[PDB]
Amino acid sequence: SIEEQAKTFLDKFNHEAEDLFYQSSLASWN
Image (cartoon, rainbow, N blue to C red; front, top):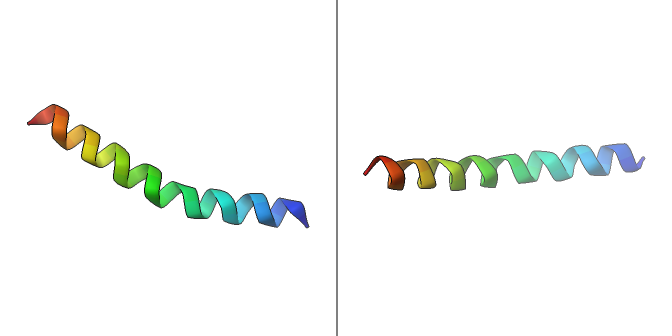
């Protein structure tokens, strides 16, 4: 039930988290 909701919440969140972290890493490297 709610476990699936949490799982899909994390599935949505991980892509944006990776994108933001990658942008921050690129900025720091530059």
